[PDB]
Image (cartoon, rainbow over all chains, first blue to last red):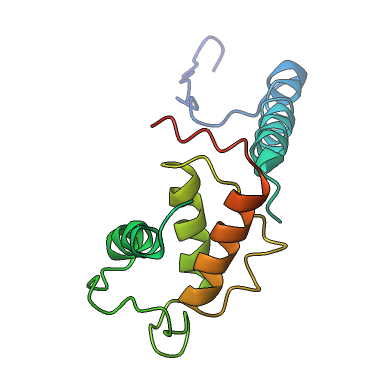
Length: 50
Length: 90
């Protein structure tokens, strides 16, 4: 018939995927980390031991 | 000039802290790897704790040529008699 309707709404709150901002901010917290580690290594290499 | 019996007495108190060998075994005719089983990964620690008490930078260029305690006492003796700039201020 006309007018009869049943409209639910599923709770899909864990089905997400990051945007471009959350990806540019995830691929920039791993590069600076290894750069800082390399700089700390270069600072540690002052004692002249290889 | 530093006496031999104080050079050995200062080296033994570091060997006993790093490894645990009693200072009654450190004699001037003991090899660092055959008689006293001290791998070089412990010789590096000994050479670090040496500088962290008396300012002395033993470079790895020379850390390989020390096979006996007599070699250590001779090296220290020659470097302290060559350079008169030995501060020895605590």
